[PDB]
Length: 128
Length: 234
RNA sequence: UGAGCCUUGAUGUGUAGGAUAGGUGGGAGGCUUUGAAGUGUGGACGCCAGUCUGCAUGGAGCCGACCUUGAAAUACCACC
Image 1 (cartoon, protein in one colour):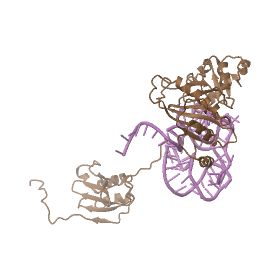
Image 2 (image 1 turned 90 degrees about the vertical axis):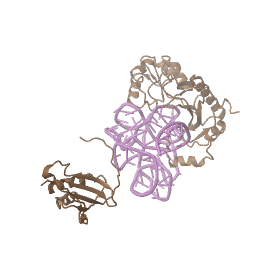
Image 3 (image 1 turned 60 degrees about the horizontal axis):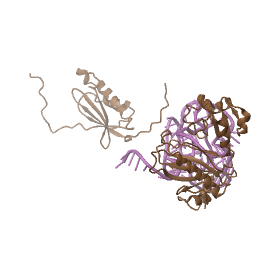
Image 4 (image 1 turned 45 degrees about the horizontal axis):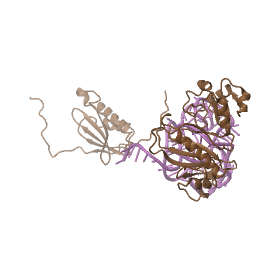
């Protein structure tokens, strides 16, 4: 039951608006909220949701990673979001849907996914 | 309390200046700064630089002023077995047990002083520590707790005034009415002063009196340079 | 940039209580724009927007020895 507690009044940075960054790889998704001038207000993951195996790199484990970070930043006092997408991995749309279920307008889905001018050689993987 | 209001403001306007003053010119200034239809009472705040810890490093007890206040000092008698006519002839208003044990439990006492027996103290007054400003519960340290009740009642009504510590070294004591002449007031002041020095601990021989200021009731106060040794204005 | 010391100035927002419980002497009340109270303005300040408070205006209130509730009881002047 209820206790006689003092009123809450605290401030952290009260940014009201942000950018989000989504790094999609082949084994996981990393999902990260920042201020628009560029400072991390929290992150979550799909690997920390504990699906493991192939199931760890799916649109649904990626979605629930997005809803985990988006919950935590209300305390920073963010109220609006915009999103940056960076990768070919799963959660193309499902990651977006979970920030939009956090109560944000997500009008700007700016793919910034870096296409190196043919970068560094990826791992061979299996020896056949 | 000393709440800042309109009725206080007028008093703060009519004064000529605030400074630490000579005791005789403070008393003659302070008498202009009464404002009331009631005749105000006059007392002194003396701040002592002592620890004020329980009793041993405190100054606590009472003295008889040579001249009494122009008030009666509203006396009750809290006891388990006395003759009512004999205490009343000494000056008491009410003698009993039950009515005074009710008041001090209730948390309002109609009397300004209760002279208490050790036997009265024992049930109600011996444990009480946080007794408020109407000063209902007994203390031994004050010396109001005596089996010789009728002597302390007659001496309370004639001119006995108290001195105590709070949680601090600060001594409040009654000096007279604004009715009174300057000398007669100095004479009461100086009687208190020998009493705070007689009670002073063996360790309190450095700086003792830190600050003096003298006060009237509804009117203001005037801060004091020192108390001095004279029972005459001149 | 902490803390102490010290001048003045103030809150204890609770649970019962109108509402406002730092230790306690004086002490039976104060009538400059009724001591008020009140949106508003600055400061103290909560166990929580409410107590004290500078003030154009506002004359509607505090509250005890005695409205009343209580284990500390409250005006108003001091000490802070």
